[PDB]
Image (tube, rainbow over all chains, first blue to last red):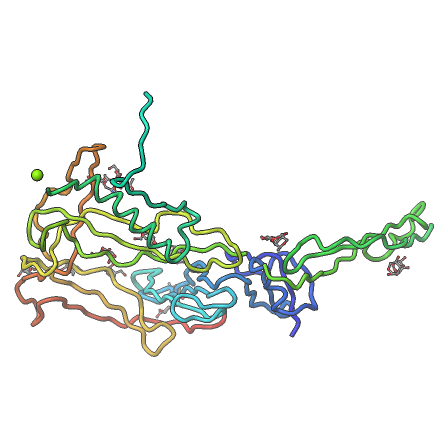
Length: 106
Length: 48
Length: 210
Ligand SMILES: *[C@@H]1O[C@H](CO[C@H]2O[C@@H](C)[C@@H](O)[C@@H](O)[C@@H]2O)[C@@H](O[C@@H]2O[C@H](CO)[C@@H](O)[C@H](O)[C@H]2NC(C)=O)[C@H](O)[C@H]1NC(C)=O
Ligand SMILES: *[C@@H]1O[C@@H](C)[C@@H](O)[C@@H](O[C@@H]2O[C@H](CO)[C@@H](O)[C@H](O)[C@H]2O)[C@@H]1O
Ligand SMILES: *[C@@H]1O[C@@H](C)[C@@H](O)[C@@H](O[C@@H]2O[C@H](CO)[C@@H](O)[C@H](O)[C@H]2O)[C@@H]1O
Ligand SMILES: *[C@H]1O[C@H](CO)[C@@H](O)[C@H](O)[C@@H]1O
Ligand SMILES: *[C@H]1O[C@H](CO)[C@@H](O)[C@H](O)[C@@H]1O
Ligand SMILES: *[C@H]1O[C@H](CO)[C@@H](O)[C@H](O)[C@@H]1O
Ligand SMILES: *[C@H]1O[C@H](CO)[C@@H](O)[C@H](O)[C@@H]1O
Ligand SMILES: *[C@H]1O[C@H](CO)[C@@H](O)[C@H](O)[C@@H]1O
Ligand SMILES: *[C@H]1O[C@H](CO)[C@@H](O)[C@H](O)[C@@H]1O
Ligand SMILES: *[C@H]1O[C@H](CO)[C@@H](O)[C@H](O)[C@@H]1O
Ligand SMILES: *[C@H]1O[C@H](CO)[C@@H](O)[C@H](O)[C@@H]1O
Ligand SMILES: *[C@H]1O[C@H](CO)[C@@H](O)[C@H](O)[C@@H]1O
Ligand SMILES: [Mg+2]
C-alpha cells in the first residue's frame, strides 16, 4: 500500500517534516532509514529508523484547582522495523501519573 | 641512539586492531581483553 | 492587460541519490506570453517534483546499549576481599547494536573498570531511612491508581579510605562499594527490611489520544 514519504522526522514533536511526495511503497521509502512516512495527513508520523522513545511531554493541568489532584504526561514510541524498550511497538503510548496540588486548601 | 630490537624466540607479538576493526564480535572480545591487560598491569603491578 | 502562460517543460533532472528514494524536478518558465501591464500570473506552478526509486538498499550507525552489571569486586591473586580493607576492581561491558549497511561503528570504550570495596553478604549495622519521595501513581490509566513511599533498613557503610593513590603515572581512582549487604536493624512495624505505605491518587484523569 502506497504512503506519503517524508524526508525528515522531527522527533521533538513527532511531526512529519519535509514532504518528498506520495504514491510510493513503504519498503522503498524506508530504504533510507532517516526518512519517515504517514498515511495522508491524518497524523501518526513514523520515522524509518530504529524505534526509540520520544521525550516526556509536559504535565497536563491538574485535574482540580482545589487540594490534591492528579496530572498525566505521555511518551510515544516512534520508529520503524523493531521495538522500543519493553517490547513496545511503534506508536504505542506510555504514561506517568503524578499527584499535583494547585491550591493546598479549598 | 642506534638501538634496534631483534625479534627472537623470547619475543612475543600479537596484533591489536584499531577502533573501527574492533567491532567484529570476535575482535570485540580481543579489544576487551587487550584493554583489561592494559589497565591491570599499570595499576596493580605484581605480587611476585 | 496581457494574459501570461507557461512555456515548455525543460529536461528532467537525474536521480540525485544512488540509494533508496530521491527527488527529481522539472522546471518551466512563463517566458513566451509573459504578463504585461498587469494581467494574471501564468496560473499554477512552474516547478514539478517527482520521486525516483533506485530500488537498492542503503546506512545506520550503531548505538551503545546500556552498561551491563558490574563484575564481582576481586583482587588479583587473592581470595575474597569481602568485609576487608582491600580495594579491588571490577569491569563492565557494553554492546554495539543497530549498525547496518556499512554504518559508522560505535565510538567510545566498550569496557569500563573502577575500583571497589567488597561488602557482598557482609554483616553490618543499619538505621531506618526517612520516608522516600512519593512514587508514581500506578497503574496509570488503570483502575484506582495509588502512590507508594517507603522506609528501608539502610546499612551503615564502613569508614574506609575512599581514594587510593597509586604511582606509575600518579593515578588516583575512586572506590565504590559493591554488593548486597545484610543490614541489621531493630524491627519497626513487624518488618526488618522495608516498610512502605500506599495512598490513592485523587481525581485521576482519563488517558486519551494526544
Ligand atoms: C572521582 O572523584 C573525582 C573527585 O570529585 C569527587 O571526589 C570525591 C572524593 C568527593 O570529594 C566528591 O565530593 C568529589 O566531587 C570526580 O571528579 C570531579 O571532581 C569535581 C571536584 O569536586 C566534582 O565537582 C565533580 O562532580 C567530579 N566529577 C566529574 C567532573 O565528573 C570524578 O568524576 C570521580 N569519578 C571518576 C571516575 O574519576
Ligand atoms: C478552581 O479554583 C478553586 C478555588 C475552586 O473554585 C475550584 O472549583 C471547585 O469548588 C468546589 C467547592 O466549591 C471544590 O469542592 C472543588 O474541589 C473545586 O474543583 C476551581 O476548579
Ligand atoms: C551511491 O551508491 C550506494 C551504493 C551508496 O553507497 C550511496 O551512499 C549513500 O548516498 C546517500 C546520499 O546520496 C546517503 O543518504 C547515504 O547516507 C549514503 O550512504 C551512494 O551515494
Ligand atoms: C522523560 O524523563 C526523563 C526526563 O525527565 C528522561 O528520561 C527523558 O527526557 C524522558 O523523555
Ligand atoms: C511538569 O511539571 C512541572 C510544571 O508543573 C515542570 O517540571 C514541567 O513542565 C513538567 O512537564
Ligand atoms: C500553464 O499550465 C497549464 C498547462 O500546462 C495551463 O493551466 C495553462 O496553459 C498555463 O499557461
Ligand atoms: C510540460 O508538461 C507537459 C508535457 O509533459 C505539457 O503540459 C507542456 O508541454 C509543458 O511544457
Ligand atoms: C553506562 O554508564 C552510564 C550509566 O551508569 C551512562 O554513561 C550510560 O547509560 C552508559 O550506557
Ligand atoms: C554496578 O554497580 C552498582 C551495583 O553495585 C549499580 O550501579 C549497577 O548494578 C552497576 O552495574
Ligand atoms: C530504625 O528505627 C528507630 C529510629 O527511628 C531505631 O530503632 C533504629 O534507628 C532503627 O534503625
Ligand atoms: C516520614 O514521615 C514524617 C515526615 O512526613 C517524619 O516522621 C519523617 O520525615 C519520616 O521519614
Ligand atoms: C509525597 O507527598 C508530598 C509531595 O506531594 C510530600 O509530603 C513528599 O514529597 C512525599 O514524598
Ligand atoms: Mg619478589
